[PDB]
Image (cartoon, rainbow, N blue to C red):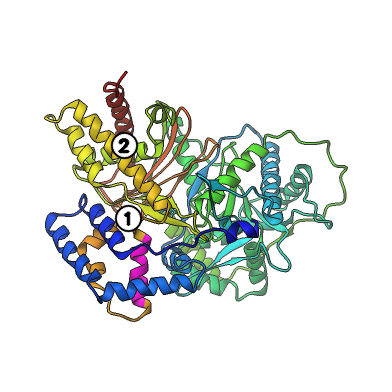
Amino acid sequence: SHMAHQDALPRLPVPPLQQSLDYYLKALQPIVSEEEWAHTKQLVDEFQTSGGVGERLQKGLERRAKKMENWLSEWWLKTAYLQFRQPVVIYSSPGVILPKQDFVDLQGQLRFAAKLIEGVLDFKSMIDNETLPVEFLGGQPLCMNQYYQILSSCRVPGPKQDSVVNFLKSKRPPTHITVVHNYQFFELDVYHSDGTPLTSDQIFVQLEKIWNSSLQSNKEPVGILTSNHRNTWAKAYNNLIKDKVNRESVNSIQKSIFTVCLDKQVPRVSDDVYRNHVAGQMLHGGGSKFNSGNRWFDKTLQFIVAEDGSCGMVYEHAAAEGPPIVALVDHVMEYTKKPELVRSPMVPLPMPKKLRFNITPEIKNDIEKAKQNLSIMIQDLDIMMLTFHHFGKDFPKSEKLSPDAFIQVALQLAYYRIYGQACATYESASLRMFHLGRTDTIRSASIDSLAFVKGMGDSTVPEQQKVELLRKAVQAHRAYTDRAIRGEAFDRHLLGLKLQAIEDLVSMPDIFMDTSYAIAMHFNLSTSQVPAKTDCVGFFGPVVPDGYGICYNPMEAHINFSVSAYNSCAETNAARMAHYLEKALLDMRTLLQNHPRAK
Ligand SMILES: C[N+](C)(C)C[C@H](O)CC(=O)O
């Protein structure tokens, strides 16, 4: 947004070596053995010894920060996503489920879909004009650069590493979106000649023509190719755009402000697994026979409107971060409720261009391969959506406790109860207080948390002592959260030293080849909060085979949880973890309330 605003932002810092290495050792203690900790302790010293390797790398990062807006920007985007060759589906692109809608027929589906498009465009006008209210936290400005990445962009396959294209602010910014129905894509202009955007009514009419221009699911699901392994997809992608029409269709999708998916009717399932499936539809689409082919997963923003009223979205992480999405969601959902205006007399409206795809025996073979790959993926994903009705932010806040810290500590209590030990845990922290900041790591497994979980279950340790261990565990977490937000966390900084070493062509340092670093970066628990005003929830796959993906939205009197795991690992089960997590949240409340402070 405002130039003055972004110009006042502090630039991402490089924390002091001794600081980050100290925090590093503290965070390792709860997850490694003493031998492993002792050895890592020795390696940590050698790394920071006078005139040693650590210093040369450290100064490298400091120089790097003087010559760049953000010393970590390109590096994070590159190593976390563009270089991640796993399919973006389930493994990277977050899935979001919005509050169900009440439409009961097709027309209601097109109507809502239309309202939503107008909603996003209203949100877009604010971003174009730079009128979107500048944001703050505690009184510190927050970078607004993430709002410019989510629209009119698209991930691009690469034989070695992908890339991201953005056209929001080009000479001829896009004015069309892409709509896909029954696997067929269309190019729909959402603005008139005079810049004014179409209306909810003008949109609905266009979507109707599209619906008609694809009555049957009688075409190849080209789009499903975007969900295969990035290396496989890069080859199939290249072979796909060897054709002029294909290339032109693809090109149209890449520049489209965003994509809207009008899903087809799917079989009915028992109620107790209904939410689970809906999430599946938003996360991955359900598979080859359902709506997976009704997607273009490279697209930064994909809004999904189900046939049964459900709806949600899925964004590609390369160019999308949490904050923008949350803001867009809240603003759009609210807009779809704001009463319209008298129908703007209808003016002549063109036919939405259909983006055809010439199929060849090779393009068709890749598609069959993509169906098969995705199918395996879905069959391995274990999801359990938990709606914690017991309480939300109200309880923790009435106890003068941060709800996020509380939930995180509950999760630690739940994991320990199941496995009898703690594990490397990750919780997304927003680095937005700094120019171009995306995220840093908050480590939920701490000295205090383990102390709390052990004691919590120790028959000898008194309830009163348990409650004190709990309060310490929560506060420790909150502090870490605040620290990570101010750039005092250490994970990104450690990554930087390593990358700096590689860049300078220096032998990989011992500190990184260390078993302890392998364990510290192997996140059996991957988490993130979605602090939305809308009663929605996010979800994503575990970052490790034997791990869980947990995402939550704390509401006032309840909490929306998503828990994911992989079937290929017998030691992890979604339901069980969700079941324990609930019990952990409740035992924590019971414990807190039975041992108050004073009167
Ligand atoms: C899901 N997870 C934590 C892997 C990615 C986060 O949503 C974004 C981040 O932490 O950079």
Judge depth for marks 2 and 1 and give the one in front: 2
321 vs 514, left or right, is right
Q: Which amino acid does label 1 sit on?
A: Val
Dominant secondary structure, magenta: helix
The answer to whether residue 234 is magenta is: no
Check disc 1: other Cα within 10 Å, few if <14, some if 14-19, many if 20+. Answer: some
Left or right: residue 201 compared with residue 565 = right
x 44%, y 66%: residue? 72
State the extent of the magenta-drawn residues as a range: 492-502
Tell which circle, 2 or 1, labels the residue nearer the N-terminal end. Answer: 2
Of the 4 image quadrants, the one containing the C terminus is top left
Residue receiving disc 2 = 410
Whether residue 306 can be seen here: no
Residue 478 drawn at (x, y percent) = 36, 42
Q: Is residue 442 visible?
A: yes
- Quadrant (top left/top right/bottom left/bottom right) for the N terminus: bottom right
Where does the image place residue 451, in percent across and percent down from the top left? 20, 40
Q: Where is residue 195 in the image (x, y as percent from the top left)?
A: 80, 56
Q: Position of residue 452 (x, y in %)?
A: 22, 37
Residue in the image at 41% along x and 67% along y: 79
Mark 1, residue position? 544
Q: In this view, does 130 lie above or below 64?
A: above
Q: Residue 265 carries which label?
A: none
Q: Residue at x 31, y 60 (%)?
A: 20
Out of 164 and 290, give the one closest to the viewer: 164
| Secondary element type, mark 2 | helix
Report the Cα–Cα distance between label 2 and label 1. 21 Å
Dot 2 alpha-carbon crowd within 10 angstroms: few under 14, some 14 to 19, many 20 or more: many
